[PDB]
Length: 382
Image (cartoon, rainbow, N blue to C red; front, side, top):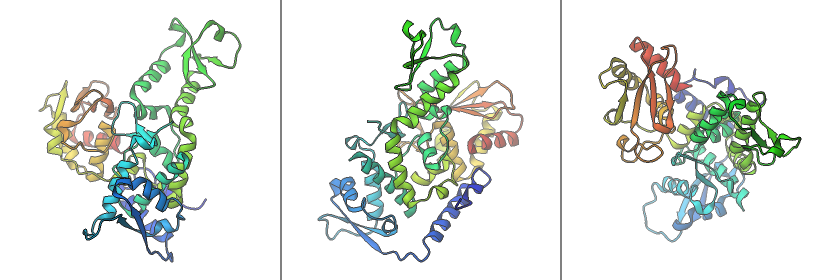
């Protein structure tokens, strides 16, 4: 053991305080390090490849130098804001299909995951860049899936994390787990070769290691293995490369102070959330605009601080990214889907819940403003 940052995990410490501590610990770890400026020469139209050439071989120590960006052949242009410009470009390039490194997650066009389909060196370099941005206190306009942030944090990925990767697939796992397989009219199998579910043929009902029959007793374990393959196994070498690059700059023990939600805010920034714009673009179901719990909801959200407002956006939409055109342009699967609040008629003992595929908040009919505010904060900060 080489640190105690883990003792500050969880919600007791506000994101702003965690952030300040995180910065101070990086500075402690760099005491006596004699930094200097390091030139990065790139062609404007090849930032990603040129940056890779210029930096991928640098030592972790050299990567702590201040980067001095020089755009090939561009002379007499103002020199302010070039590093910021470079981070914005490489953020876009770090998601370009032509490099085949990342791809959008099923359903959510905002969030990216590692492409399961040279390459390992580039993944390591991307991990380096993400850590370098965080180290520099500069933002990347790159959003990842929940399980990807957990990987960075050293946290165990669970089948519930599949709700961020792929909502429709998660629905299938939910159906499987909640219903007795013996009443299907057919049998499921688990393939040991690809770690996916299938339908048993007669020969699978006989002894074999190719397709294991799924039962009430074993389905939870196979749901676990199917999820582990999709979120970890299928991208195991790439992930390891990315992580190796990230940790060379930001130690695992240090970054682990943040939750999955807070790591996203650290990488891609704390957005400003225009509550009037959101409110003008909210739909209500089984509540009306003037239902008392709705008036309480707006008052509570407005009472939240910047970090908690952003975590609220993450809670209901799946990401902290505000749409370019404002909340009138929030999207679901197949087009626009405005933020929507539904009355949850189950016990007022429950926390509000969310269905991010539909930007939907399920809000119990709480009995007081203070309870609503308290319950919503719990739901969000989890």
